[PDB]
Length: 112
Image (cartoon, rainbow, N blue to C red):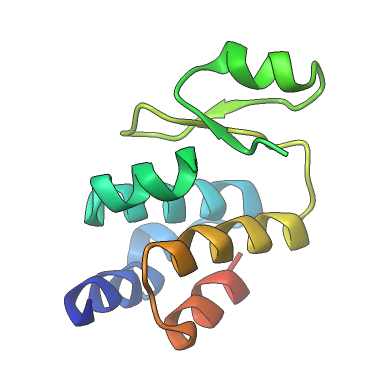
């Protein structure tokens, strides 16, 4: 887990992440990165209100105004009809389930 923590820390100080001025894109890059780091763990944590799916329609079936969006470089979709607080909670839920320690989770969610 220490190397996974290191990867999330590396994201937070990366040029790509720093350049993002909007919460939605930071949210998305965080999710993409979590999947990159451990796709199996990410899959379990997200497929476990429904926030995530492996297709757009499932999320539209949950609600027509959920504004589902594809998580880049993954097979997954996430609802985006939400504020930054809710985005933070979603990322926390995922990262807790994937086994991350709270310290890095706080830094990652605060960055959204």
